[PDB]
Image (cartoon, rainbow, N blue to C red; front, side, top):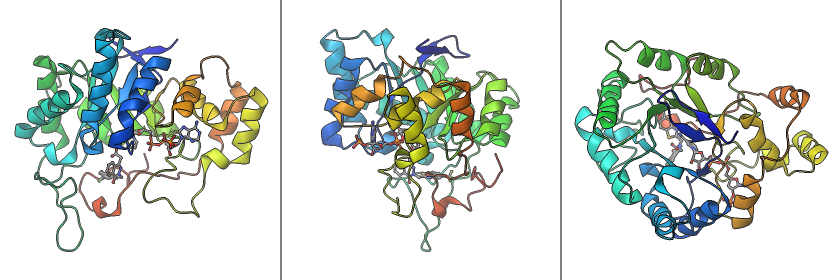
Length: 315
Ligand SMILES: NC(=O)c1ccc[n+]([C@@H]2O[C@H](COP(=O)([O-])OP(=O)(O)OC[C@H]3O[C@@H](n4cnc5c(N)ncnc54)[C@H](OP(=O)(O)O)[C@@H]3O)[C@@H](O)[C@H]2O)c1
Ligand SMILES: O=C(O)Cc1nn(Cc2nc3cc(C(F)(F)F)ccc3s2)c(=O)c2ccccc12
């Protein structure tokens, strides 16, 4: 089907629109187009600096009665400089005000690592190290549970948490709400079989980000591999008369994942949505899995000393 059941009882569309790097002056039309062609799930974050512009689109389509609020699945994330107990609600409310919403369908802890609070998203020390905060993921989680009890968010989850970090939450003394989602990087060069099996076995839905390999990531290098240009993946697309992006989106769907491709190009927003009329074979699926190379697009050097850095752990 087009939605997956979460452990809070709500249904989540398995295809959503990503918004990182979408320019503020193009994202409003991108989201309007996406809602017109069928998207019902938008992935957002405060740190993306465009939630106000995303919100304008949502509100105009609610106003035009193109969609009802209950049909939408809007996701945002708590940035690293707001992990303190005291700061979490205000951060949520700023995202709700920008998005012109009175609740979120899902709010995530964006990364396991807390950073010093302040105006800078990445506060650095004089030698370029991120300055941590002395907060821990368990008290931040409790702060997230309160947002559920206050009606601000319907579900809470995590992002970029490794298996020991998910387990820390699942084992939290006094845990009130389990995380509904873990949103992680996932594509054929980073297949994440171990972390996905762990999360699914715990009834945690996995959302796959950068499913096209984030070719617009700012730190991309020409020497970097390219999923969209991999002729083996092109061949599989060509077998099904689809584009490579369409194969790349359909692949996590058939692993019972949610996937959130980003685009601000209307033709591609539409193309990326036409992934419900074809299936990859089980053989196609194992072949795509075989391209794993443990290549990660999303990390940041300056954060690697943080005690809560998620990617030293194998998974
Ligand atoms: N939780 C987190 O830490 C985290 C981290 C990274 C990403 N995310 C979320 O995941 C979303 C998707 O990840 P991403 O933005 O890193 O990258 P992505 O979706 O893997 O790739 C986006 C790039 O692909 C291009 N593209 C889209 N559709 C295409 C198509 N059909 N054919 C060819 N190129 C196409 C886009 O170009 P145009 O836009 O120019 O069309 C853009 O340059 C993000 O936007 C964000 O919402 C979350
Ligand atoms: O975050 C987005 O959605 C995309 C994203 N990713 N990254 C790469 C990152 N790598 C990290 C590693 C840690 C770590 F936990 F490992 F310390 C913590 C935080 C980060 S940000 C960025 O630097 C970034 C900057 C602005 C807006 C979005 C992003």
